[PDB]
Amino acid sequence: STVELCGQWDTRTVAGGRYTVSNNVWGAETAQCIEVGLETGNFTITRAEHDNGNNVAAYPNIQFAIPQPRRVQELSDVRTSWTLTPITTGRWNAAYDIFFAANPNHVTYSGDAELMIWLNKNGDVMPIGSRVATVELAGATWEVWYADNGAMNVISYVRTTPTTSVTELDLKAFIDDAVARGYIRPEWYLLSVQTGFELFTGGAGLRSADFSVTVQ
Image (cartoon, rainbow, N blue to C red; front, side, top):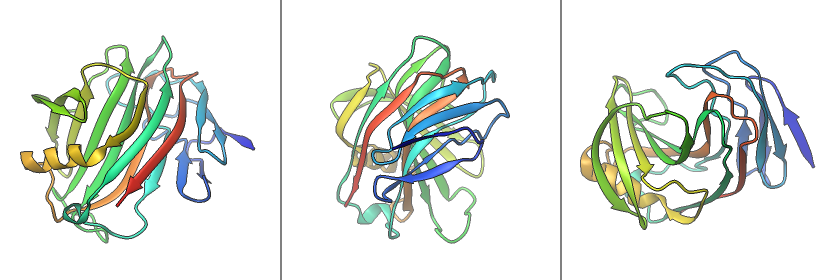
């Protein structure tokens, strides 16, 4: 079965409790609906009236919360698959968002990080931060962007060739690279892995499907 979520902060648990799908209109009050498949977690943005400037309006997403606390240094394998369906209009990206914290029990200033992996976009949208490098990871080339705003590092990897599909993408390769760069500490905990669309203007018709995450 399916359901349409139109509330700003609506969420649903899907896929046998493994993932959560959220509307997540956090940066605007403009309307948005997603239609969610409750067995798969697949979703289609059916409504999106956003018209933001340089800041994100919304990030509807599917999330895997790590079930038991795990330090980056304790991970052996992190894999993910995903298929997106792009549209020809609007300003949006298709991006993973991975969160790390020193302390699962309390916010830690400068001890928290956000790692993004951009697979696709439309319009003039760019990451938060400065462009610092290019790297070869997981069979492809990525621009590396870095922001040290204050409380939280943002590290973004932007695929130089846009795509709509990844299968068994090695997320640990990205984690290991950010560790090599000093942006993530090995003792930090991996909290969650999300993917979806950062919406700036429009977004209706974007589709997320076939999401899977393995953390060993």
